Image 1 (cartoon, rainbow, N blue to C red):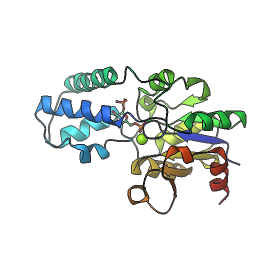
Image 2 (tube, rainbow, N blue to C red):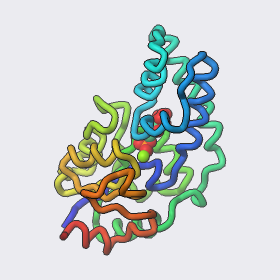
Image 3 (tube, rainbow, N blue to C red):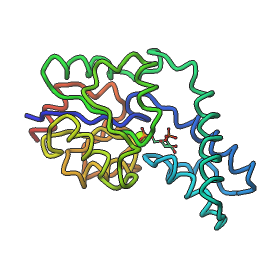
Image 4 (cartoon, rainbow, N blue to C red):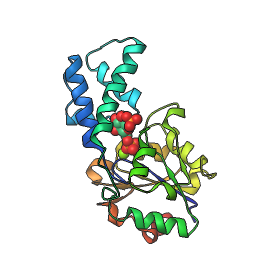
Length: 218
Ligand SMILES: O=P(O)(O)OC[C@H]1O[C@@H](OP(=O)(O)O)[C@H](O)[C@@H](O)[C@@H]1O
Ligand SMILES: [Mg+2]
């Protein structure tokens, strides 16, 4: 039996991707950079604040001091955080609270494995903090998804190996990170976007405890 689930935040528990996109878009327009469209923002998900900024600058080969790097990242995040102020336990995706409840009551460890440092804040606002045995700190990892570092760190934060764990994700990068940690990915979305070599569910209401047990088994 699997001993842990490792949850991505955005696109599994809820999704604030629209707000990250709007804030990043707004910042690029302010610094004169074209190309931050929705297509580009697909490669920004699963990706850290620092690495998302760098991808944006790289669009125009734009060079900045480390100080003006910090201020630009701070500008974007203040904007983003202003846009997620009304997030509540209404925003939690279908089946996720029940699954968290069923995982807890069966002694299955629950870890967050998000690239966002606003993760703690959102789980608080959604009243989900209590269910989480650990929240992997994206400040402390060496690389963004698809690197496996975040899911490895998450698994370790609940004293289990990734091989004892299930990873839940909406993104290609996230799924690839799960694969390379040694955890079992179960995706949510379309198999045209994520693949046909893994189990995909069409929405998060399909993420039930009995279904996870079935998949684990094969
Ligand atoms: O899918 P998840 O890993 O949960 O979220 C990924 C998001 O993390 C955010 O970090 P932040 O909140 O600015 O520190 C990034 O700025 C954003 O570009 C990215 O889409
Ligand atoms: Mg995600």
